[PDB]
Image (cartoon, coloured by chain):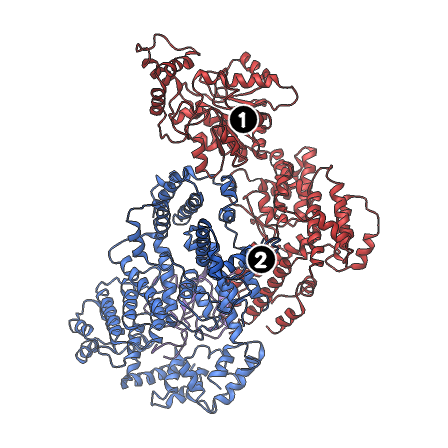
Amino acid sequence: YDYHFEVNGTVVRHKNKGFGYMERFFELKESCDERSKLSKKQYERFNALFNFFEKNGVICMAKDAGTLNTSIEINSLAYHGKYDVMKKFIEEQSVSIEDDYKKAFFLACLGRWEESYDLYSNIILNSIDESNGCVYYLSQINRYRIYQSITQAVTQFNGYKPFTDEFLARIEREMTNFNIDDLFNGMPFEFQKKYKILEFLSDNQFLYDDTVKLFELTNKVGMSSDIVVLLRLYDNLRFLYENCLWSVSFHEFHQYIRNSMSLLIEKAEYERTRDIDELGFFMEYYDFVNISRHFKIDDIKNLERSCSIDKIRFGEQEKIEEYLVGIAEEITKQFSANGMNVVFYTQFISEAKAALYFAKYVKLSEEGLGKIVKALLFYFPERDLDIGKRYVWLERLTKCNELPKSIISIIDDFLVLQAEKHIDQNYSEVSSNGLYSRDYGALIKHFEKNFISKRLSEITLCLTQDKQKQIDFLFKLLPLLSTNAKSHLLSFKSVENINDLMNGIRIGLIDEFTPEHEELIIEYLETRKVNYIVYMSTFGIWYFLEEINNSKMEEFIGMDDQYDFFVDPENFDYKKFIPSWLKNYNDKLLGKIAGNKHMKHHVIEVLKERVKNSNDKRYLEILMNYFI
Amino acid sequence: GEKLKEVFLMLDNNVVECIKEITESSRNGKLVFFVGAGVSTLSDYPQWWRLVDKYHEELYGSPKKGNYSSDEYLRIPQIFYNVKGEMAFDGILKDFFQVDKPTNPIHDKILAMNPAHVITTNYDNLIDTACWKRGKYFSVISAEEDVANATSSRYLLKVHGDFRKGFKGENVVLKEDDYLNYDQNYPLISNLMKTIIATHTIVFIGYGLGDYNINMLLNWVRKLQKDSFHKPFFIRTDPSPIENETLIYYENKGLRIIDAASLIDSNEYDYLERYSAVMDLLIESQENKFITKDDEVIDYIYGKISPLFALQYIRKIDLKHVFEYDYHFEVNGTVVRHKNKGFGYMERFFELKESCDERSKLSKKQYERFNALFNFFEKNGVICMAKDAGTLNTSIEINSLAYHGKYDVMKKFIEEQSVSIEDDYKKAFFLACLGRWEESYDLYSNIILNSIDESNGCVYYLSQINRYRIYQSITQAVTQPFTDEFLARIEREMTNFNIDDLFNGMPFEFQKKYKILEFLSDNQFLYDDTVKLFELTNKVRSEMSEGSYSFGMSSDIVVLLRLYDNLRFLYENCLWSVSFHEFHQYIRNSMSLLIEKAEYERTRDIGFFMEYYDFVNISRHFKIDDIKNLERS
Amino acid sequence: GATHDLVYHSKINTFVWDVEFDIVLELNKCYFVKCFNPYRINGDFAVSSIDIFSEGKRLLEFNFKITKAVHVATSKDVTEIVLHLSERISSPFPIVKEVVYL
């Protein structure tokens, strides 16, 4: 309870009754002449204390400032991913017990919990005799942390056996009464005052202080509180990762980082959008790593549905590119041959899903997007990310960047690969969205519009009439293949199917109105009249956008009011048009309803009425963007 | 499991009493085990007779004719030490005692009885390294200067020494030679042994009745006075059942024999199951699987809830810490089960609460205790468990005249004469609220001086805490009214206050019964519901961007009822720490995010109905600018 | 009586709630998911795209007169409420079991 130590490296005085000793320290630090007048041993001690306070960033007091810069730098290979360097660093021989300590933490990170437990126990057994019991004490703490980790691994994953039941019974035999609360208060007299500050490491809910500081960033507030909480955040991460603490992975910490950059991004949203009156948070590499690692996929989605992150600028794009190329490369090595360590799998897949979700806003390069898209489509596993959500992620990636030729070639390789997996007539094509491989075709038809498939054309040329699903997969992806191929599978056609090939145009038949089929539409409307006398809006929409040229659909008006609503807009009574009916139209179709004259005059009244009723803002956003 | 249940059904009366006193002394944190060789040799540790063998055949040649008597176990190696030499003696000790034997499983359960100290007569590294593995610290003492470095308050008293400082015969008591003049070489381990023995509950496990250590101790306690010492316990695990006469005799010298051969039916070389028979009979008594009938459940609740008959209102987060990591107590009054290994005692409590007929079949005194526990749990709102619900209603009601303003009634309540020290306590808090800090300080000091003699030290402890709180209040008042006589007097008397060990200086009764009040000696105990507010961040405040009229129960009612739990705690227990900035910070941000989430709830159309208590909270804990900020948000 | 799970997801006017349909459009064990892609490339002109399951895709014709709906993990068929919410909402597919929100 001496000098307050601030979050920028400045020191202010508080409750120090006595000589200003930090003040004489900094004055002796500034001028060299007073620094000279001293004996040898404590000049060396001054060099040591000097190296300490420059290493922790603690600089001269609040009397002199202006050059206050905080370049944060976590120098640890467990923060930057660096997993192949981590394994490489494991296999060498140790020379010290500190090397044993870092190797234990690294090996604990990449899904290997047993050998890190044993190496922890080796540090306990081989440092108890030697002084400075911090490495010892931290080893004990971390050994219990990894014990809780392993028992969490049999708490969840048995709800495959990751560890053998010899080890799982041994540690449960030896660690099942652990009461850490008096561990530090059993340490010697030296380790009860010198390292008395480490007493929160025998607990977990020590996160309370900066958590309440986040509530200042709630409590409804140059230099703001943002830089305070951000630098205290980086103080926390640099503590738990550079001191190699295993308690960084427990849920309270991810809770804290989660909510921390939640409220920082929400406050930058509440900062630049102050422009009622007159008319921030610049991302770096560490913000990208924190967003990818501590958030979840749904939470980044929640940030996108709360704060406009498209405004938020991004810097240091090359190191972020190294993190994404590294993360995709480690996906590639994760599923090249083997190595499916289920522990490391669950962690690394959560990070890789979140990072590839957040990689939309990043200005990637040529070969970077090459390795990322290749590892996303080919090597990236199922049962977490399926083939529809790879259009979510992939189309998310392949929209902000102008698509190079090689990327379309790789997606073509994916389509050929899916055709080669449609050679078995049991291929399910599972999808948790409803999006399928035809959308992959639509992607290539969006960014190239003139793409002729070559090897897929060769597959359709050697296509045999014994594999129906294979043909179907060649038949949904229809506008990609050559003309002789078109002769081949357009021979494989059934034209009497009115409303399969319609019902969802499942093959992409919107390429042509082959005129007997539009006369088929017409005679279908005759059959509607026939089974009247005593889905459908799509027909009407196909009249609305000047696509079918026959007009006698006005004869078939009288069964569906939406049919009248797209065929004869003038004579239809705009007083019983249900509004519902508009939350299910595309932007183009709503744009073309907005492009009329007698339509707009009434739907502004009904839509403004339903907006005016309680709070409907789909109708107000459509009303402010399409209809206005 | 069931076998030991039948063992508990077939115990003698004095045996059951001994299981009670060992168990409650384990619960007090005062239970010192004096263990021996028979515990350590089931880890296959080499006993002393093998060394009398090897030192013997390395002395005389000529292996033993008949058998050794008592003194030869000390005499023959002594011969070796005097004649053959130091290095040969220490070399043979170095050979036989260089073992890396694993631990006996009863070591796990000795260290699972929460011992205060562990006094041993062993020479190994089993109990201590087992204590390093089980995350406790016992002060491993094996020398004179090891006593001076008493690094903790939990002692592992190796009274004979240890081979930590090398395998040297100088370091341990093995020769005769050290049993002769033992009161001249280890005077301080002697004094500490007498100290720990006289001030605890001592349990003898691994010995023979007539072993020389026990003979020395019985000599010393028979030199002591007779009203003063606690009679220790002797757990006898021998192959032979003890006869009655030596039992009665060793009851008269001061020990209490719990036999193990008479409880089970075991073999001759079957030591381990007999040790584990008695030791599991103690552990399962802690874990209360021996609790079967009405008078056994209704007391174990009572023995933890009758302390809290004094306080006005207890939170439902801390009531989890009453029944230590048992049943989760939810914020609506429901109880779900978690980590309770043993009889469902709350379940029998609520079933006895529902039907009157089972409620009838009980003795008088604990039917009255059931009425008391019943009045408690209805007063704190704790109702029947999660099996039956639907009428879950939470009508919050802070019945305090410091919450509703009521200032003229407060002054009126001040000027009457007190009849109790509780009336003194409420008058002190009320008078503290309405700007009168000096007389409330003096009345606090009156409660400290006039309740220290009387039991149930909660009112005392809370008075101390609140006196320091009002001291911080007054020094805040001269930080940012009072005469400089008072302002120098309290600054004279309260300027070294370190509250962190105040509760850990309270008696043994006030260290477990009111152990849940330990956060009141701190301030940043607001952490939990603060992070729960961040659930109301973490985007179940997602519910705007997708239309969702989700009809059910959200996190809003959870955080709101936990908020009202907090306010009802700090105002009905008359705590002065309600006025410090962290609490206004918490209520501030709490209804900030509740109102912001109701804003993020009804505007999902791509709630939060105010009552009186919401109006009072908005007026009191917000500021003017913050209510303006809520209107502009 | 499963109103404690019934939502009214109203960007697309659905009722996301796990039932299991038995339809005649004759089938058994049908459940529905719906999309919300208003930026769908070349995929008709509608945002919502139903993806009817019959333990896998039906490969879809359509009269959808539901015969038997039953709520998962609490039984006693909820068919009257399914007809009532079918009567109120004039849209395709009132009871959808999941929503993607692209």
Chain name for mark 1: B
Task: Give the answer, above or below, for where A18 lies relative to A389.
Answer: above
Residue B577 falls in image quadrant: bottom right
- Mark drawn on residue A485: none
Three-letter amino acid code at the position of disc 2: Val
Residue behind mark 1: B188
User: In the displayed image of the protein, which residue is found farthest to the right?
Assistant: B416
The tint of chain B in the picture is red
Three-letter amino acid code at the position of disc 1: Leu
User: In the displayed image of the protein, which residue is found farthest to the left?
Assistant: A462
The tint of chain A in the picture is blue
Q: Position of residue B23 (x, y in %)?
A: 56, 31
Q: Position of residue B425 (x, y in %)?
A: 75, 48
Kindly state the secondary structure of the residue where label 1 is placed: helix
**For the residues carrying marks 1 and 2, which lies nearer the camera in this image?**
1
Q: Residue at x 41, y 28 (%)?
A: B163
Chain name for mark 2: B
- Mark drawn on residue B558: 2
Task: Give the answer, above or below, for where A69 lies relative to A240.
Answer: below
Among the chains, which one is purple? C
Residue B198 falls in image quadrant: top right
